[PDB]
Image (cartoon, rainbow over all chains, first blue to last red):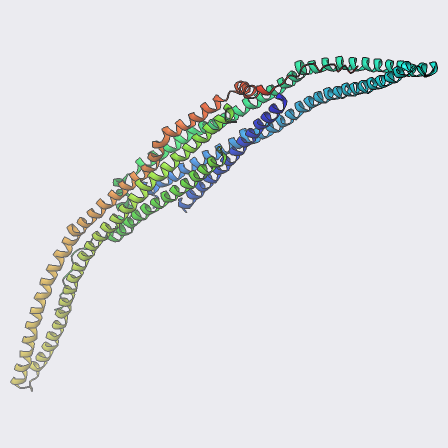
Length: 273
Length: 273
């Protein structure tokens, strides 16, 4: 009974494993689609004038957003490897080890069942043999009481009875031996054989569970790894914004252009006379 | 000259403003599409068995990922407000203030140009008036030298000359006054009038530049604001993974099910005889 339960439960353990793997695969894809659009966006507004801080910082910011997208691709990459690829391989291993333990258990059950079939046939053969001996005893008996039967009639019927009696005895002994044989095997089957199989499944199940736990961890671990650089990115944007020097951009304007500011002097008198 | 340059430059300042606004709007949309898929994902694997830590932590993790999506929506929300909405309104204000300063400048140029047209007409009228006086002087002169002309011929032609001479003098004075008038205005135009307009455009431009700088800042500021909760989210996932107690889940299994583990005893002997 504890066999069918472990069977459904260990299968459930692999199913959950396979779902987590599936959940991370999609997380990976969702993450990548995002980074993609982030790249595209940066492409769309980046320079196809660039002397003023205003136009400068905007580039520096587009740059850090572009780096940020890089970090997200890094997470999608690591998860895809440390989790999906690895755990998918590991789920295949455990799916197989599980199969092996159950085959060993089934073989154990089959060996005992075959023992039971032996028990059965010997009991049956004992029963029928008992009936014959009884039917042959009733016959010999009745003639024995028939004062008109001959001594030969009694002798013959008695022979058949003694004969069937011995056969029932022999059949009884094989039934008995078989019973003793079966009971020991069954006892041993439940005392050590099944417990030993249960241990293996408990061991494997616990290993998958622990490994599934580490898989859970890789989800947050991949995020944590990129935390520092994402912080670098954010700072890079904060400095860029504070780099915008409005009063100085003005200075730069009335500079490269001033050489064209002509201040016309007084118009002259046109004496025609 | 410095007018047309400031004209193109201040327009460029508003254009860059409008591009940043545009860049953030899309960032907002890219961010939202991401959070959406993140929500959908969590929906897809969340519970439509839940007694084992393994199934537990997975939910707790799906929960924190779901919260994470919330934080991203929060950023998309804030940017959409503090940047897009606000700066779009502000770009409209500055587009209008800019228009106003240039109209004031154009009016200044038109007033001077109209002054020049006055100068011109007076010069022209002086020139033609000079020629007449000259043509009339050559006529009076020639008759004056003609010993066969009469005194009347000379007198008449001289009258016409003196007359045209006075008209040329009067026209000269109006040309002169006009010149003095124009030169002062032009001088004043370039000394104070245009400088005063330039200041206003410099002031406005610098204000848009500074404001555009703050807009740049809101990009990183919105990220920083959610940094703490995103950290909470990551921790929530790390604990969940470390909460997976494999050895204890086993315990929970051979519990709610054990009441069904029947250990069959010895089969009994069937004495038929």
